Each structure stands twice: as structure tokens, then as C-alpha cells.
Image: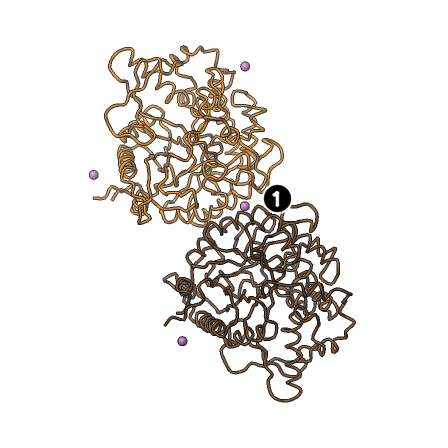
Chain colours: A brown, B orange
Amino acid sequence: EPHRFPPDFQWGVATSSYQIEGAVEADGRSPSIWDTFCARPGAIADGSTGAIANDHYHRYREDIAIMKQLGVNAYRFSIAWPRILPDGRGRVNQAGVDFYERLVDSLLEQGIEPYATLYHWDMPQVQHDRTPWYDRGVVDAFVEYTDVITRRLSDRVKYWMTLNEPWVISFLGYGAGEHAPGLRDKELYLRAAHHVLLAHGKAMPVIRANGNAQTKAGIVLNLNWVNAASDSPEDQAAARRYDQFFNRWFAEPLYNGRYPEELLEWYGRDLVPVQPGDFDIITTPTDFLAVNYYARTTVKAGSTDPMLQVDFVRPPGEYTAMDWEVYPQGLYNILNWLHTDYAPPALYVTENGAAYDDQVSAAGEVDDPQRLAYLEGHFEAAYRAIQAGIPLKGYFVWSLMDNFEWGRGFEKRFGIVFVDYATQQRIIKRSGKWFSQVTRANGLP
Amino acid sequence: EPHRFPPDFQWGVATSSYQIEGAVEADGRSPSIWDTFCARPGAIADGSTGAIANDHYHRYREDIAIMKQLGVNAYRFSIAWPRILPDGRGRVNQAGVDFYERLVDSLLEQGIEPYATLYHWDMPQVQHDRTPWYDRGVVDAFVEYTDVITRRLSDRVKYWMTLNEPWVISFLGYGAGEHAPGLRDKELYLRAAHHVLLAHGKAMPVIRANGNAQTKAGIVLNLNWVNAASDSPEDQAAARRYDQFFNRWFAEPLYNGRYPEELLEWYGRDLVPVQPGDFDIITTPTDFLAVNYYARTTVKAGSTDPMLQVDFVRPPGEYTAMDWEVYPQGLYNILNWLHTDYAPPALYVTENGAAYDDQVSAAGEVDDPQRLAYLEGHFEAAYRAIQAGIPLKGYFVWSLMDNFEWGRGFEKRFGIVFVDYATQQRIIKRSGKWFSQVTRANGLP
Ligand code: NI
Ligand code: NI
Ligand code: NI
Ligand code: NI
């Protein structure tokens, strides 16, 4: 049954720098906000840090060989600002730039297209000391960083992502206190959210300028399918607020030059530090929109989250180890919504995947049928989306291998490749072996 | 009935620091004389250096796991003076000490006994600038280094070797110009030879004092079986001079407090800078004598080596890729000579092995029957020595894996484990798989 994807479809896997690289003091790297945050009691559920991680800084070539086994034609990673500009600004760290040159050279040598994320949450601590995301001066700082690295890599890297998951950077970082730098303030989150958008917009012309005609760039948004727990007006309203908060807070500014009004009013409109011309910057044209999709979230009115006055409900269904509902149809729905409402020239699924408890068998294999079924359903939903004329150009599985899952530490494994953290051994999981077939087939089954 | 070795016999593999570690600039390491010497045109046959080597500095855990596969109960390695005291003297480099602590801890955790060589040719360049081996001040410099590292590791390392192959350090380094520092002078070689012996003697009481009742220490001598090309007086005399030059120059001082007199006269006795009390120092009692044996060397009167007035002959037989004659009987003869003439309380074969051209087969294996046959014959010779009552306590194969073979570069492979230098992949060779059975059987199948 030829459920084949388009002939140039990009099949990849995704990682982020602090999640896999380790080697946190190597070669002039300065501490990121995450290096500092992991020190805080209760911040990381298993008490771990990203100090070693997958040790990908040293093991990249081996990982690239794994990718060859996987059959991917694309690889999404992030570049660590602390390696490039350890003082946050000013002097370029040659050694740091050199790592990414070696990585990109190795990828292209193996026929793997590099998709580079500029910012995936690891701002140098020294830069955050000067300009936290709630401080407008952060925009120029991120742009300087973008300029340095893009000038060095634009000859080899064609696809760039500006910032990964604005909602996470702003809300979790500054609103819920769950991610670095670990603050919890509604105003700080809204300021951070606005400045992330501004940084994305100011960065785009820089990327295009340091590139060539082939250069493509966009932002990466986390989106999930949102449902109301019931038909009650309070629940419909709760769902609508959460949807505006999670899914529309960035998309509407990016495409329509406005924040969702009802949520804006509810917050207090003056808390967003919009200045004249900001929306013109924010709406700067992009080549694509990248989407990170994981789950359906079902909402009712309540007090669990005091800021939005909502509670979360779990419909009967299948759940991952992250307590996230498995809802493959949600991916189709999100792609369709973006395509009908904003009409981006191209879409990419830059992240999709699942965490389940994995064990290594006596045979030395990792049998993960739940994760495989998860991936299968979502790939199917993406295939349906393409058949419906949605311009989905690629799909990147989160993640290549198990890694530091932020506040959950190393306890939640998202990889299609298992990592034994005692020895750094990599074992391709059953889902990974299956994926090796999908990529070569292009794709299902 | 099986040819079984004694129940506590130590089966091991051997390496040296510059040959395997790489990471030449890491963690405060300063350049050794070999880092400088590799820069010299014509010094290394394939134009290589030890800058990366086997990358064992990073890959030690993996290598140790290979050792477990091999079934060894002992591991001989060397410690890099440039890592421990990068300025040659004075400030201890704790990161350097730390690598060796982690290496030893990991070995003991796997039940592998560490046998540590203090000096295996890598003097820090900065120290050599102050005290080359021909300068008597080198003795106190080596003793300082010995003291620092033996204090840090004596609780875990019981077996220590002071200096590896005095003949090489002095003759190849200062007499033939073939090894670092690359000088070619008879006087400089003899001064160096004498100071190495003195460094060995001064070091012993330091190692004993920093240790406990279990501490065992000795020197490591290269010895080969020597034959005269014919019965002519000129050939006998040539063979005698070579024997005295290669085999007796160090052994006679160590055990009898004298240099071989005829060769001494031949050179000019004033060139050896012997001072009163030196022989009392050189003869300080040792726990064992370690032996590195490879070949039979056949000599005739000739002008090829002008210093000794000798030529070398190749008898009909089997030759390795180093152009060294395979003569397993020689190993027994050497051990028997040392046992009868000097009666050391214990003997170890700290090095024995062979270099043959290896290829990786399409099946991904390395089939090396010539290396296997070499090892078998020599192990048999060692078995015979033990049956004759020679107190051989252990046997270390040179080497665990292919490595930087000094002046021959990476082109000569001595390992029972193949290294693909493009990726650092280790493939246990056929000889290695065979050895995996010998260690477990504790004798020859
Ligand atoms: Ni169909
Ligand atoms: Ni027999
Ligand atoms: Ni390193
Ligand atoms: Ni003198």
C-alpha cells in the first residue's frame, strides 16, 4: 500500500544543544541560563543537569552515523549561543564556531541537510544578566549573535529557524517559573513574549542578507489541539482563553499584526510593551512555518492555573509517560487550521514524538511499541494533510535519541535511539528501526 | 593435558600515553618532546603525529570494556609527565592527575590490575629545555614527578615501572637521532644512558616510601636474542659488541654495578659521567625485572653502523612488517639468561607482539593469522620458561590496539584490536579473539 510522501519530502530527527551536547565548560563555552537553573532545588525532577547529557559535543560523528542508519535526509539541531559568543556579545569564540562547522561539514558529506535553530533556550548567563527576555535590549543582542553565526555558516546552511517555541521561552521561563531563568510573573512573561517576536522579526533580514537566494527562514511554534471539556459557556470560554494563550498568541502577531484581543484585555493590554513599528517588524515575511505538535489538551473552567482560570481534564484515551494525551488527528487539524487561516508557503513538522518508559531487554534491544504506534498515527495524519493540499515539506521526529528533557531531567526518554547514560552507548529502538524503513520507503508503511 | 599457566598468572595488554591518548592540548597538558619531534621533516615515516592517536583520553571507558572482552586481568599503561606537571616541575595539574585517577578507578572496578609506567618517552618539552637526559639534573626532575604522582595513586596502584627501555631513550633519542629529541652523538647517548639508570635508582626509594608493604617496582628493559652471522672472529666480536650495546649495557649496572668493560673501552670510558655512589644508587633492589622482547638480531662485522662497526644479516625465516625476525625461542633464551645470571625474584614480559599488514574484510573482520601464530609461539616459549622454574609472573601483549608507532607512524599496526583511524572504531582482530580464549583458559588451547 503506497502511502508514499512527495518525492523531495524531508524526513529528519531533531535535537537541541543543551539537551545533547554536554561538555559545558569545553572550548570557551560560558554557562547558559540552564547551567545555572539546574542548580536550583526542585527545578529538575531527577536532580540532574545538562553537564554531560549525550556528550554529543565529542560524539557527533558517531551520532551522524546513526542518522545514516536511520535513513534521514535532514537533521534539525540548535546552535549554542554560549559557545559562539561566550561573553554574550563581542568577541567571537573561534573554537565554538569550529564545532558547528565540523558538524555541518560532516552532515553535508553524508548527504544530510542541516536545519539550524538559532535559539533553543540556552542564552548565555552573562547575557541574561544584561538583557533578560523581558528587557527590550535582548532583541539587538540576539540579532548580533545571529549575524555572527549566519555569516560563518550561510554558505553551508540554507534552512534557519530563529527561535524555538516562543510560548515556552516566555511563559515557562518567566510566567510559570518551570524553565530557566525560573521567574513567575504575568507581566514578565508578556514582555518576554513580545521581545521574542521582535527578535524573530529583526533577525530575518539579517539571515537573508548573510545568505543567498536559496536561504529559507522561519520561526518554530509549539501548537497542540485544544478542546473544551463540555458545552457549558464557562468551559467554552476557558478553552478559548487557553487556545488564545497557547496557539494564537504568536501566530496572530506573526501573520495579522495583532494579539488575540479577548485574552489581551483579560491580561491588561498595557502589560505588553508594544512600540510603534513593532508589528511591521514582527510580520516580516517568512519562507515557512515550523510546528512542534505533541498532544490534545482539554480544558474546563477552574482555578488550577489562576492566571487563566482553567483546569485540565483527561478524556479517556491513551497517555504517554509525560501525561500527554495521544491524539494524532490533532496534527492534521493544526496543519489544516494554519493552512486555511494563514496560508504559509511551506509548513514543516519540526518536532513530534513521545516518551514511554523504556527498558533494555536481556537480548540488548529496546522494544517500544507504544512509541512506534504513536509515530505511525501521526505520520498517517501528516500524510492525510499532504493529500489535502497542505504544503508540508518535512517531518522531524523528536528526538534522535534520549536526552535531557528539561524540567523532567533524563527520566523522560523521547528518542528513537536509546542512551544508556552509564556508558553513553546508543541502542537503536524498535521504533527507530521501523523509522529506518519509513525513511527509505518514503514512507508508510 | 592443557598447557595451563600458574593460577595467579597475569595476562595483560600494554600501551603508552603518547601512543594512544591524543588530546594533546586538553586539560592543561603541555607539549612533550614528541609533540615537537613530530614536526620535523623525515622524523615520522608517514608524516603523522600523536595529536589524536586512539583518542584514548576521551575513550578510556570504551577501551576498558574491550579489555574485559579480552579477559585480561592486568593492564600496562604509562602516565604522561606533561599532564601531571605541565611546567615540568612545580605546580601539579589536578585535571591531569584526575584523568589517571578515573582511569585506575575504572580499571580496579572491572577487576583489572594496573601496572603503571612512570616514563615512556614523553618528557615535557619545557623540562627537556632545562634538563635533557644528558644533563645530570634530569635525575632530580624525574624524581619530583615520580613523587607527585606516586603520592596521588599509590593507594590504588601497587605495581610501578620506572622507565621504559633505557636503551631506546638514550640511544634512539640521543645516539641515532631516530626518536625525540632527535640527536646523534655517542657522548650524549652515553650520558643519557647513565642518567636514566640513575633516575631509576633515585626513584625506587620514593616509590617505596609513598607506598606500602604491597608496593612492587622495577625497570623495563628491551632485550632481543643476539646471534653472530658466522664463527669468524670478526663476526663473533661484532655480535659481542652489539649484545653488550643492546642487552647488557643496563642490566650489568643494575645487578653488578658495572658497565660491560670491553664496549666501555671501545667507546672511551671517560664519556660515561659516573660519579662516586652512582652504582650504589643504580643497584637499589627491585621487586622484579620487566622485559620487552621482540626478535632475534643477527650481526656481522661491517661498517653500516660506524659507532659499533657492525652490519645486520637476515637469516632465512619469517619476518614481520617491521622487518624483524620471528624467533620465539629467543624469548625463552632471554628469560633463562636473566634468571641464571641475575636471579631476579620475579620477571614479567611487559611487551611482546608483532606488526603485520592488516585489512578489514568485507565482513568487517580482521583476519591476522601471522600475528596469531607469532603470539602462540612466544606464549609457548613463556610456558616453557615457567616449567623450567623461571619466575615469570605475567605477560603483556604489545599492544591492546593499533597506535602511533613512533618513527613508523600509524602505518605499523601492533594491536590485537584494529583501529580505523577515520572513525576511531575498534575491531577486535582474530588474534585478539584468540587471546580472549587464552586468558580465560589461562593457557594455550
Ligand atoms: Ni489509502
Ligand atoms: Ni605438553
Ligand atoms: Ni574533550
Ligand atoms: Ni660532567
Does the residue tagged 1 have its C-beta within 8 Å of any atom of ligand 3?
Answer: no
Residue under the point 51% across and 77% down:
A329
Residue A208 in picture, x, y percent from top left: 63, 55
Q: Is residue B308 left or right of residue A220?
A: left
Label 1 crowd (10 A; few <14 / some 14-19 / many >=20) = few
User: Which chain does the residue under circle 1 lie in?
Assistant: A
**Location of the C terminus of chain A (image quadrant):** bottom left
Say if B373 sits above or below B440 in the image: above
Secondary structure under tag 1 reads: helix
Residue B7 in picture, x, y percent from top left: 32, 44
Residue A212 in picture, x, y percent from top left: 59, 52
Q: Nearer the viewer, residue B32 or B276?
A: B32
Say if A408 sits above or below A241 in the image: above
Q: Is residue B360 left or right of residue A143?
A: left
Q: Is residue B61 left or right of residue B443?
A: right
The quarter of the rendering in which ligand 4 is drawn is top right
Q: Nearer the viewer, residue B305 or A153?
A: A153
Task: Give the mark count.
Answer: 1
Q: Is residue B441 left or right of residue B308?
A: left
Residue B33 in picture, x, y percent from top left: 52, 29
Report which quarter residue A43 is drawn in: bottom right
Name the residue tied to disc 1: A94
**Location of the N terminus of chain A (image quadrant):** bottom left
Q: Nearer the viewer, residue B254 or B405?
A: B405
Residue that extends furthest to the front in the rendered view of this protein: A213
Q: Label 1 amino acid?
A: Gln
Q: Nearer the viewer, residue B255 or A181?
A: A181
Say if A335 sits above or below B382 in the image: below
